[PDB]
Length: 113
Ligand SMILES: OCc1ccc(CO)c(Br)c1
Image (tube, rainbow, N blue to C red; front, side, top):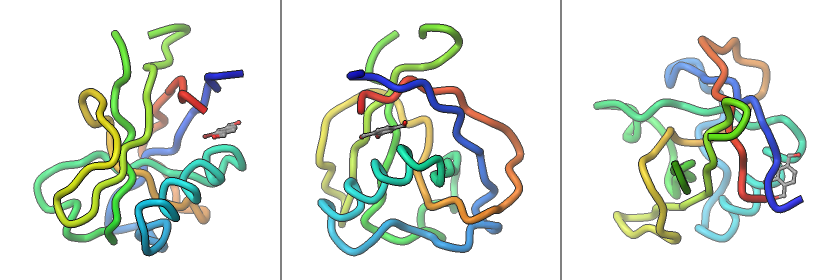
């Protein structure tokens, strides 16, 4: 399937234990996709003060369209030193590894595998 329905745990930035997916744009997009497949991916909502508390390169989910079965359609865009790899819509947040942090909410998304 070109798209997969996922329910991502929304984590508070200060709870996150592993604050990024790796060291290159290609590695972070790779690892983010693997963690989304394995159900070990969390989401941090981007507000003032959040990104400096996380590790670059960043992986964003961005809205790819205007929402089947409650699931917003999204795609991945990485960012490193202010350059973005991918072009998409509004940020829904920044992806991080999930290693058992308690969420505050769940965000239903339809991910373009
Ligand atoms: O089942 C969730 C899932 C499965 C495969 C891929 C491949 O990219 C992704 Br992303 C997410």
